[PDB]
Image (tube, rainbow, N blue to C red):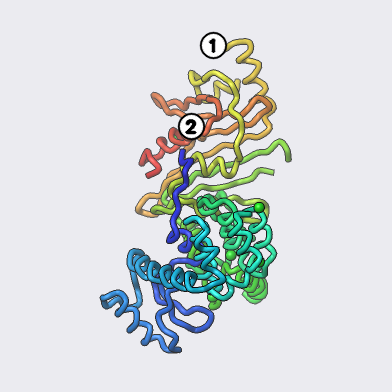
Amino acid sequence: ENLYFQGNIFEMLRIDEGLRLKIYKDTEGYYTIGIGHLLTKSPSLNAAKSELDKAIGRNTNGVITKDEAEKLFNQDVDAAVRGILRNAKLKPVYDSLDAVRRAALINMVFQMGETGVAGFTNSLRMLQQKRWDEAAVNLAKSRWYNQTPNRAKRVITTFRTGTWDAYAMVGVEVTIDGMLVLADRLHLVDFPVALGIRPDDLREIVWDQVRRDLTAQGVLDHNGYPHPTVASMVDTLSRPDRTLEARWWRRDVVMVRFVVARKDDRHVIAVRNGDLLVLQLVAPQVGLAGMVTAVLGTADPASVEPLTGIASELAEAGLAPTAARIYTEIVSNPDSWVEIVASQRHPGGTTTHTKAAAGVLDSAHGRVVSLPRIVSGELYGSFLPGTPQNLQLALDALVELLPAGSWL
Ligand SMILES: [Cl-]
Ligand SMILES: [Cl-]
Ligand SMILES: [Cl-]
Ligand SMILES: [Cl-]
Ligand SMILES: [Cl-]
């Protein structure tokens, strides 16, 4: 599903710049709200509260809604486009670009300013000549690219493709200690046990180096607070409403554990590789099957018949000779084996995990998915060819075993 990924300039910059609903202080000391909407230059806080109330037409106490931040953002986009169209170095390139690549260019102005963007003289001519691949390579040769790697990558991919796909799943990579530093800063505990994120003077020198490193990546801001998008990722993993928790065994090599977590409308993928954690904030348009596929990769479905009239562990103790030899090789010697359980959080702070699990098998004959069923009080198992549709079916069945019976 979701073969045409729909983005827009506001969601793009919400992710890259970060949406702040509370008055904020950038590095230069200026008070800011929304997506980098400058409130005042004054070194004073109260001046900022005055200016914010004027722009909103409401007494706000330094707190706005997402809709209000979008209003301010639209004015800033106009101001940035107005500036671009009056800059002889940027107007020709902007006029030639499609709407998506225009948003990528507006994205850069938001970050480094109209003059800084005009300094990419080589890349700007490549974009005007529709040499997408060359511009993408050239842009990566800037200090901008290394200063903010995750943002520049997405913007450069957007310049290359002219699509929104770079924002379907946006990822950050942190060490287990960096994750603990973020959680400590955000008042977060109760992470999925499957990720193994567990809680003086020696710890302080260790974390002050990690904090310095996170600041260098733009994961922590100038006062040591996380980027709002990273904050969103880590928060979603703390006390999620739903999770898929997976154990992933790879014949080609240690078991990898990863999680898909939902909290309200946010989805986060968390893969742990040793002492490394990869977090991905996932756009609502993506489906559960797509999130799992993002971790496991694509594979050709194994041309097999269904094998659902199977009781629990009876599978492991009326098929064809051919259909029997295929299935035997799949389970006996699989290239890869994933088991996925699901959980849900209850209002009272407790959680339920399924006992049954959905399965994904890769082999020389193609991928296979295993769908769990509780019928008449006994656990059933059904093997199906591993298409993204059947994977979604296996995950739907798994989730239906939760007290709520749905992912919502
Ligand atoms: Cl350049
Ligand atoms: Cl090119
Ligand atoms: Cl970044
Ligand atoms: Cl900052
Ligand atoms: Cl169960």
Q: Residue at x 46, y 71 (%)?
A: 80
Q: Position of residue 222 (x, y in %)?
A: 55, 77
Residue sticking out furthest to the right: 253
Question: Neighbour class for label 2 at 10 Å: few (<14), some, many (≥20)?
Answer: few
Name which of mark 2 and mark 1 comes first in the sequence.
Answer: 1
Q: Position of residue 346 (x, y in %)?
A: 37, 50
Q: Position of residue 9 (x, y in %)?
A: 45, 60
Q: Is residue 135 left or right of residue 81?
A: right
* SS category of the residue bearing label 1: loop
254 or 350, nearer to the observer: 254
Is residue 55 at all visible to an observer of this figure?
A: yes
Circle 2 residue = 389
Report how far apart the C-alphas of labels 2 and 1 lie in the structure: 25 Å
Circle 1 residue = 318
Q: Residue at x 62, y 40 (%)?
A: 248
Is residue 202 at all visible to an observer of this figure?
A: no
Of tags 2 and 1, the one toward the viewer is 2
Q: Is residue 318 left or right of residue 45?
A: right
Ligand 1 position by quadrant: bottom right
Q: Quadrant of the C terminus?
A: top left
Q: Identify residue type, mark 1.
A: Gly
Q: Residue at x 52, y 20 (%)?
A: 306
* SS category of the residue bearing label 2: helix
Q: Is mark 1 within 8 Å of ligand 5?
A: no
Q: Identify residue type, mark 2.
A: Gln
CB atoms at circles 2 and 1 under 8 Å apart?
A: no
**In this rendering, is residue 360 above or below 276?**
above
**In this rendering, is residue 313 above or below 84?**
above
Q: Position of residue 384 (x, y in %)?
A: 53, 25
Q: Is residue 246 left or right of residue 68?
A: right
